[PDB]
Image 1 (cartoon, rainbow, N blue to C red):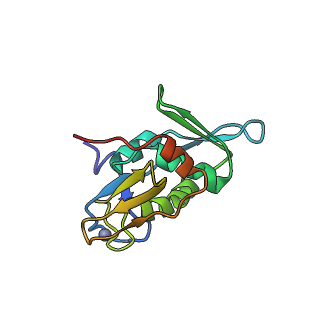
Image 2 (image 1 turned 30 degrees about the horizontal axis):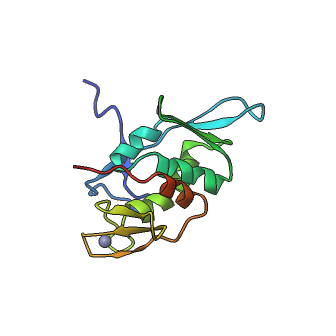
Image 3 (image 1 turned 60 degrees about the vertical axis):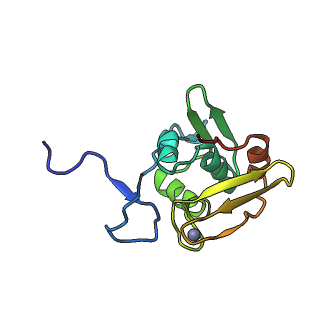
Amino acid sequence: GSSGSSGMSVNVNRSVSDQFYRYKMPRLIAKVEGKGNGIKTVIVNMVDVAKALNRPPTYPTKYFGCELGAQTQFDVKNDRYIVNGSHEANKLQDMLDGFIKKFVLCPECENPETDLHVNPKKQTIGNSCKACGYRGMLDTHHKLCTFILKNPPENSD
Ligand SMILES: [Zn+2]
């Protein structure tokens, strides 16, 4: 029984420097091959991190591409996600931070106990927080929105 744990997780947010935060998320992993001759980043821990955030990897995965300004591959069959370009986990984490700071967490209470809503008629995205009581329409993204609309989030029973 090695001294300690096997896998360590970081705080839901990269702004807190304490060990009191209950909710935790597994540090995403980014893989890279070659250099220039077809170098691309593959977020192996794309599906994992998602589940933890109670959200699909399609939300974050897509983001990376936007910010990075590159293309991305989506394969549900093998749940494999690829992001054109070279980016180390360290960086990817930061880039995602933002998303996990507004989408996931609440801009009022910063609680991961929030959700998102999609309107096919109004064609506008909006979140609703219960912890504090915040509501509104998320700034219509550039491409993401287009994807979200075409394919709404998964419902629960
Ligand atoms: Zn809130």
